[PDB]
Image (cartoon, rainbow, N blue to C red; front, side):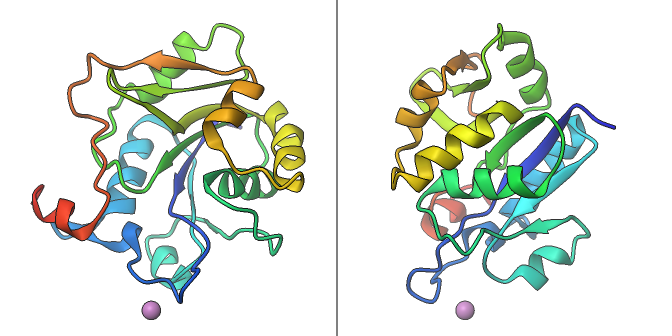
Length: 188
Ligand SMILES: [Li+]
């Protein structure tokens, strides 16, 4: 019964027994992933999180936690696909767990600027953020096909799928990434 599902991408792999769980690093006392989930819930009713480590911690805030298929596909697209395979509904707005300042018109502006494309993503004036992306259902089989072929490249997929960047360069700093604990310490 809603148009777009919000999805926090809180990562996969655990390639050495994890290391740092980025989504759980705390900014002003609140996990980065929750900053992102709260920003999505401002604009969307149904928000879920894709997480593959420490799932019980993610589950504590009461959102649905979606794990990756045992297929173990590489990179951010694997989590997008896992979520589409486990959630109904025609549209998904993905956002990595490390961009805590995303704005309340994210979904609105991406939707306004879609212009018939099945995927659009954010361009912040300086770079693409291809995993901050509004993605139609119809992308699911193409993603499955891409991943089964052993591919991983996100931008390449986004181009193959026929998407385009949407210009959010006027939103100063809403798309800053908090990539490491060292970076995080600067935003407290
Ligand atoms: Li651990």
